[PDB]
Length: 124
Length: 213
Length: 214
Ligand SMILES: [Cl-]
Ligand SMILES: [Cl-]
Figure 1 (cartoon, rainbow over the protein chains, first blue to last red):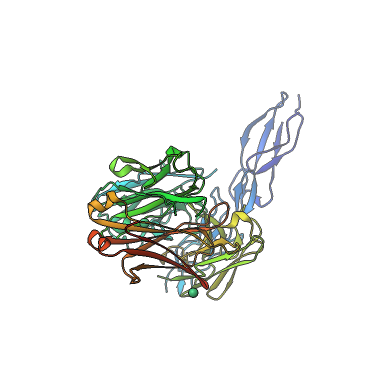
Figure 2: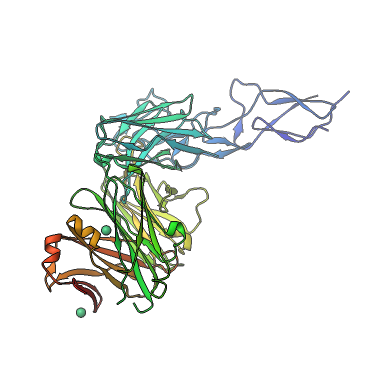
């Protein structure tokens, strides 16, 4: 049979082919990105997994380690569900707690209402 | 495994210049801040410079601003510290570390700023006949520059009971140190004691036999 | 430049004890404080980040705490491998302010009192030809480090003409050894007869000495 395989942050169960496209279930704290193709992979009668289409990604606040999604260490953030690691808190910010999506700005600092969360804070 | 391997340190004259490298394996320099932390001999850690390819900023300690330049080449995952207009106080071990809370460090590289190269004079600290069955003898290494000098005894055969002291800068501006060893008083007219004092900066090795007087 | 005042600068402790090193910052620095351990000749190792979070792999006995501006690192039961030097570092603002370090706390092994063997070495005749006389006083394998060494030439207390150097705790018997070199001119050396080294440590003063002819 085809082995139970964890690949692309998604679990693919052990499966037997048929004389065989199977979908993958996203792993804990990983999700399918909004406009993206869901994890699918093909099983072959010789016991081989073939042509992986699509992937899951670690959601905000989590990053990819081995083949799991793990919380951002305190001091780091990840605001989108991207292929990136956790990013260190930017200039003029305060150390974030675990699983952070952004870092709080420092007393006396702000980021304009337009600016994203991956941006340094500026003097008010 | 995240790894930091440094290079480039060594001997340099004041006003000359030097370049230290920091080759990183196991992670991407672009996605990380990298810092240079130096330690002068016998002192604590001092911050030198910081770099973030992502946010694009290059920060220097007030004490080195405008003489050192930090840079990085994300292709070769290598960060550079160029040191120009080098002074006496710049003599230190220079480390590169990853992130602000620095979780991985390089091994360090030693930067020695020397105005003069002077090899050591060695004088015998001759032993006494007047502690009963233990006598102390050694080598007095005087007036060398720059650091360091390494002292061994009988080509490394004596190690038990050896104390090599930290060097001191003397008033004259040259370094100075002593090595001593304790030995049974009885094996004094029978066992010979040579100290092996070695000063790479002048490519000088002195081998002196310390004898009873 | 937020100064980081580390206290103490040195402490001697036994294995199993609770060590507590303190670091008071000059300003609010949030939790942007870290703690490192350095063993001699080796690079530092991150111990605690965000002032209270264990790095991965550091033994559980290490911990860090905050109150306002006073950060304290604590070791619950000191193990033999924890004899090293410790640094607090603040990184407030993640680059917006200079990264500054504490000054360090060296943690040494406690031991029983041991008096030094005191040896005094005259100048060598080979050095004397050069015109400088170096008189060396050795204190060998004693505890604790603190000792007052004074130089006497013909019962005259010398000052300004000596220098000391001290080792680090011996790996086997945890003792220190100390040298004191009196540097004199050949003229000065030959104009007096009796040179003496005084080691005082508590209520006792050993004095070793020599007579230029003997
Ligand atoms: Cl000395
Ligand atoms: Cl007394």
